[PDB]
Amino acid sequence: SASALVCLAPGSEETEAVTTIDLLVRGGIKVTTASVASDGNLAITCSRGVKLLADAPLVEVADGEYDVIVLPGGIKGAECFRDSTLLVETVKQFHRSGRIVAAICAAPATVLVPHDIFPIGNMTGFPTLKDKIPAEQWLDKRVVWDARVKLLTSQGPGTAIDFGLKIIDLLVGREKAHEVASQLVMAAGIYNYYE
Amino acid sequence: SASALVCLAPGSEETEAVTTIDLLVRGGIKVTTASVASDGNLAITCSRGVKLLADAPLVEVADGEYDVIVLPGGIKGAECFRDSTLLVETVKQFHRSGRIVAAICAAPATVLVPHDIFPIGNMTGFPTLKDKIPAEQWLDKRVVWDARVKLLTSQGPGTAIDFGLKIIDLLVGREKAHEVASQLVMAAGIYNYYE
Ligand SMILES: [Cl-]
Ligand SMILES: [Cl-]
Ligand SMILES: [Mg+2]
Ligand SMILES: [Mg+2]
Image (cartoon, rainbow over all chains, first blue to last red; front, side):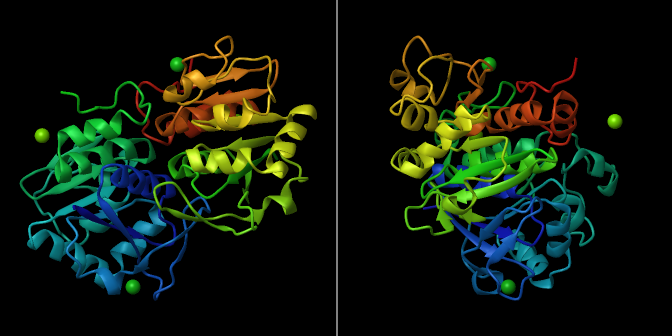
């Protein structure tokens, strides 16, 4: 079975994190949540005060064989990720070992750009943080999949469904992505993977 | 100054609960989460395994000053609500005292219909449970607001943004709903409260 490592830090965006986890589980993907930048504490207070319990400290799962590492947004959570040497090294290791990096909202600009992880990759993120992403790399699009570098990015709380569905498509296929999308009562405008 | 009591149970739908909480906080609404777990446990495992901490057991906060009571879906969470005499009494008290009841996905058919809390009024819920809503009450709309009985209902995980925005409209008004919507990068199929 496919698997995903979803990172959480103080100040992570809870709608982004939780919607993604839920969709991945609906897609049959095994999800582990990891606490980042908390010295092992598993209780994470998210950006609007929602309190989540992570499964494990990052340092205990960073070497696992997950197919994708997921970086939720939330400006303070993304800063924690950026400033965690373990988080940054783990993202680089996922990439170098042929796996997927997935990041939403503030995470592309705050984590990926300062560390030059994908120097010529195409990416999106929260629109009013556009200028934190190099102009030659920026696209203003609900989801961007750069297949060359296996980088999936997305824009905000309202694109979390689109983001999760594309992870499902990539790890377990279009039919499963459509099956999950069909469970949700999705808004018009969001791609449902039927075609 | 507006406030919302968001109920949580083992098996609640985490996207529905968390998206709603996040949006209400963005709207300036004070949110209290209440566990309906039969033992008073606050560390709730949701329908896809997300672990969410409730602020308080329902018995301690049910008599608080809250403008709306919110019932997330998730079939097992909704069954817990249905089978909790305190939950049912609290919903009835919100309604009889002129306050708002808000319910999504399985919660209308599982909680409201069997207890006959709203014998007259329009409502929606998850489409596969349509045949558990009385035919004269059912509408197939992303959100249904029946002001005659102050009943707000909605359909599924993918309508959680619509649902939260309508709570904001009802508690704080259209200007705040549009402000919050504008933050989200939400899909074109969700009403954005701008005219
Ligand atoms: Cl750690
Ligand atoms: Cl509609
Ligand atoms: Mg394909
Ligand atoms: Mg003003």
